[PDB]
Every structure is written in C-alpha cells, then in structure tokens.
Amino acid sequence: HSFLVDASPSAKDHVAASPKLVKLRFGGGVEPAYSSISILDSTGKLVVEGAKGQADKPRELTLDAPELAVGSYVVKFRVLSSDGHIVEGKYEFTVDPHENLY
Ligand SMILES: [Cl-]
Ligand SMILES: [Cu+2]
C-alpha cells in the first residue's frame, strides 16, 4: 500500500490564495493513469477530478486546480499502488481571503 505521506496543501491548512495545484506524495509508487484526486467544495460538489505524474517520481501525483473561491475544500484521493493495492483517503483545507471580497 502506498499511503499518503505528504500533501500540499495538507490537512487543516489555511492558504492565503487559491492553490495552483494539489501535490500528493505517497510511501510507495502509484500508477497515475489509474489514480484519482478530486476537490470537493464545502457543499460536497465536485470542483475538479484528475491526476498526473512523472515517470521518474513514481511516488507523487499532482492535480491542477481551477481558481478556488474563498472557503473550505476537501481533497479526496483513490490511488492504485504499484504493489497492486488500492488506497483511499481525504483531507480538508481552507482558502482564506487575502483582500476584501465583493
Ligand atoms: Cl517507490
Ligand atoms: Cu499494499
């Protein structure tokens, strides 16, 4: 099992602006073409799903995010580990305002 070992943003982080991407790092290889990352908004609506990786960094995945409105989000993931085992997980982060919102 390739468990999550690091993330950006990570669980319970507040970020000052919308993240350009979500970056996940696992404890073993994952297969990007058979892995999924999703961002959910604070109502649980699907904002974006996907996953990309680079062959020389088998333990990492990224997801390009659209511009995220201020508020809380959940990142969920469901990855296929290189040892053949599926891993799911999820965590929350918050986009704080960095200026007044109109
Ligand atoms: Cl590895
Ligand atoms: Cu395993």
Image (cartoon, rainbow, N blue to C red):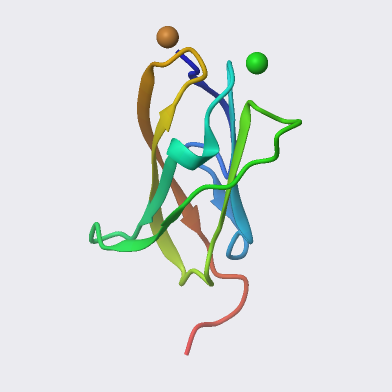
The image quadrant of residue 90 is top left
Which is nearer the eye, 67 or 26? Answer: 26
Which is nearer the eye, 45 or 30? Answer: 30
Write the residue at 42% across / 31% down: 79
Image position, residue 88 (x, y; %)? 35, 28
In this picture, is 73 found above or below 79?
Answer: below
Quadrant for the N terminus in the image = top left
In this picture, is 1 found above or below 65?
Answer: above
Image position, residue 52 (x, y; %)? 58, 47
Ligand 1 placement by image quarter: top right
Write the residue at 61% across / 78% down: 99
Which is nearer the eye, 40 or 37? Answer: 37
Q: In this view, does 21 lie to the left or right of 81?
A: right
State whether residue 35 appears in this view. no
In this picture, is 89 found above or below 65?
Answer: above
Image position, residue 102 (x, y; %)? 47, 90
The image quadrant of residue 76 is top left
The image quadrant of residue 43 is bottom left
